[PDB]
Figure 1: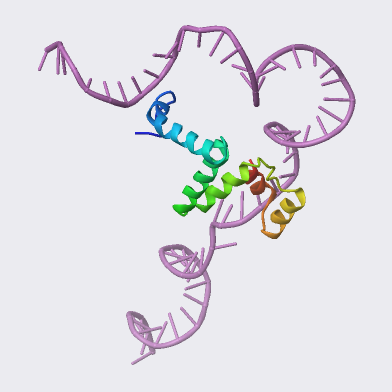
Figure 2 (figure 1 turned 180 degrees about the vertical axis):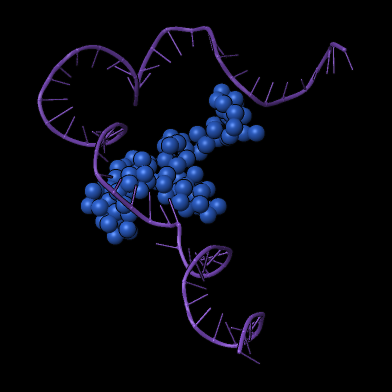
Length: 92
DNA sequence: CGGGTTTTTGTCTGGCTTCACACTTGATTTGCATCACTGTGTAAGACAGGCCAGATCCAG
């Protein structure tokens, strides 16, 4: 079952398709394999109605800091009736 | 009871990455320990004793 083996074998299996994608990228974008594969996988996720994972992927492709400032954490801790102990529990 | 037919993979091989890898040291940020209290335990039932009430016996 593919997507479960290790490397150097799944390659040997998908070598034909990989060289075809390489030819297509060379013909279209001259070798921009990374971007075209990213777009193909994003649309493949969107086809199966998996917007959450696709959004997470397109957000991490930037690699960004999704950290909340302490004001927002304080607002959440106050306006939701949370004791400091339970908030610390959730935090850890 | 073991001859063929496909996966499943470290390998050779040297030349290239993005990553990895040694003292400071003063603040700076986490992470953990410490201390005085806490809330849930939350209505009835069995029994002895005193008390009159009306019944229990006694008298000429």
